[PDB]
Length: 344
Image 1 (tube, helix red, strand yellow):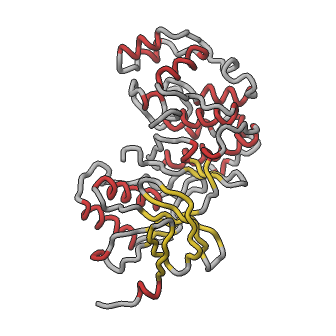
Image 2 (tube, helix red, strand yellow):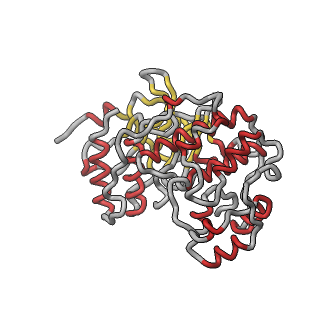
Image 3 (cartoon, helix red, strand yellow):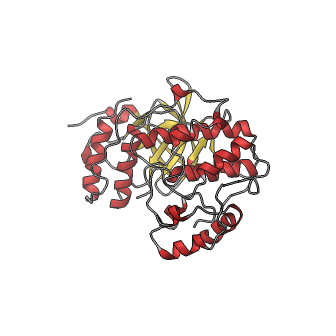
């Protein structure tokens, strides 16, 4: 039938030449940024005076790829409940029914910036301890739900002036590069992957926080990896045997063999505990590399460690449609049901 819900509950405003339609409680929408999949405004929840981030999905029903990604993102954001993992305060559409459903919005905690904006500056070790501790807590959590990031980089780590950290954009890897944060087994596919793909990235980010320099930077990854392995050395026959390719085998065999790792030449100014953690995270062998839960027990983190904060997901993340192909309309119908049944 006919209804006044929409006109009473929502207002329209142009922000960054894009039409936004928001519930009346969210005021003063201000452009923050844009990507391929959405755009973000900050707004004030007038009920409390608090700042939130609102993401308008960008034409999510233009293709199956976009619609499926929007679905999986919504599901992930709804499932995760951890302080170091970005989550949902609200989702809504202006539409009163499925018939009229074309647009939706995600409401999230506002974070002023991200680590990419700070890279190049040398961080004090206590700042590294606190920020990397938060990264690992967040990873422990998503990993416990069966979710991996797989594309962790400074741009994906939201931070504020108090060094609070949230992880963004996890679980969407299956849905141009000169600085390389992905695990070598992911970039070069030379070995089976596990959840410690994200621990390698933490290592690269921590290395960069320490020195001010990107660890792997240049046109060709393998050439940049070599520069480091020439200084650091590689693991032995137990590692080489796991390699899925004899050309990868020859590459590793041609590098210096070093029984015990020592990142002293690599990071001369790094404290002993920093260097030791770096060595255990920046580990080529995927079975030897620390998990998040293991890295959290490292003495590097003692000044900030609170085991109670190191939670796990109560339930595994469930996405039966992960490998499915549906039409745009079928993805839309699945998304709509998830918006309607949302509750904070």
